[PDB]
Each structure stands twice: as C-alpha cells, then as structure tokens.
Length: 264
Ligand SMILES: [Cl-]
Ligand SMILES: [Zn+2]
Ligand SMILES: [Zn+2]
Ligand SMILES: [Zn+2]
Image (cartoon, rainbow, N blue to C red; front, side):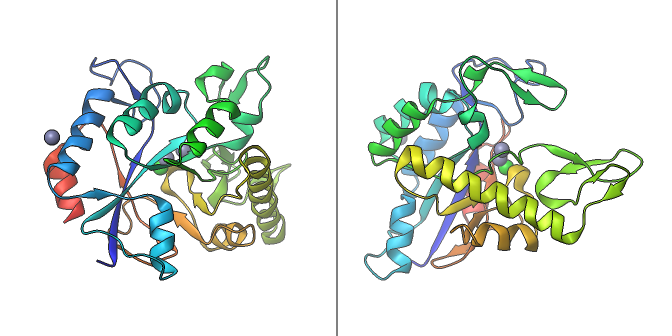
C-alpha cells in the first residue's frame, strides 16, 4: 500500500509497577507492555518497516508491505539502549530514535538542567551507544531539537509554553518574529551538526517535543534538511511522500483496541 502508521514511545522500563506515583517521566511504560504491542502487531498482519523503506518507497526504489508501521522513541533516555534496543534486535524491528542532542552533548561530569531540577547525565544515552544502535541498521537517528525540549515564559503573567512554538517573553518584552525564527533556525541547525558529527548521517526527520509545532518551526527544520516531521495524533494516516507525519502517543493505558482503532 501507500499508507503507514506511526507509534510514539518514550521511556520503557522493566518495572511492572503501576506508574502514576513513581516519578518517571511522562508516558513511561513497562517492557511487558512494549512486548505485548510488538507481539500484537506481528500477530495481526502489521509489518514494522524502517524509515529507510519509507524513503525508498517515496523515491520509487521499493514498495512497502501491507499494513506498514514505523516505531519511534523520543528523548534520549538510557532505556533506549538498555531496555528497548535488545528487544528491537530480538524482534528484528527497526525504529526511529530522537534524542535531544544538547542532553547527549552534556559532558559526563555534569547534570542536565531540566525545568526546576538538574538530572544525572545517565538518565540519557551516550553517543557511543547511539553509534552502535545506528550501525545495527535497526535505528534511524532523528532530531528532537538541540536545546528546545523545555518551556519559555510566553507572557508577562508568567505563562510557560514549549519553546519551539512561542516567542519568548524576557527582559520585559516579546521576541520579535525575526528573533523567534532565528532561535529555531540556529537550534535546529546545531542539532543537525551535533548528530551528523557523531553518527555520520544528518538527521532527516524532526520530531517535535510534546507533539507541538507550527509553520515557523516547520520552515526552520526544513532549512536544516528535516522536511519530514513527526507530530502526535493530530493526523492519523500518512501516505508515502507526506512531510507531516502523525503518530499515536503511547501510554500505560494503550491496549490492543486502542492500537487497532488507530491503525484502522
Ligand atoms: Cl511527543
Ligand atoms: Zn505472537
Ligand atoms: Zn515525545
Ligand atoms: Zn520529547
């Protein structure tokens, strides 16, 4: 066919504990739930394809199988390497991984400023780990911004919005449209270079933090080679060649009927 679905995952842990009170990051699920999805896909005729097969399809080099599905993992959590990757290898499932590049670029001796707190560097993967995963041929490296996976103050009353989608209010004023666009263009361009130099491939997908984007962000990403962009459930079916790619956001309540209705 000419259609494909996309699933969006974040962290995956061995812990089967109920998660609501455990202080993980949002949308963290259990490895059992992940396996259940991986089993349900293959036992229902869904074929996991790599991003390369998508690109090969749009370029008229090969066709996709029926009920094509892409798997995607956001943020750069060490669980990508420690929990997810062994499972991808066991299933021979490829995937797209979107680490925040300034998090990875943080030296091992430093914490990562993250809203009100500072995180141990090994919450996240190292670049050695990313190289190994990419070299397997199973994992495509996408961008998830360099350092725009945070909020900015978006008004004088102290409202905070994702940095990608809001001119910043600081020094008692709003960014100019030109300042705001510049902020996205340079961050995205540093992300592309940060990934390229470790990995050998410029990323060719932008994955938006929190699913949120706009026209300025799209054009900023496009300028650095990321015309394909991954959002969340604001679009369900993707056709070969689409720039705007929708995804299902996975959470601990995502059961088979949820996945089925989406992929239907
Ligand atoms: Cl997301
Ligand atoms: Zn099975
Ligand atoms: Zn995400
Ligand atoms: Zn994210």
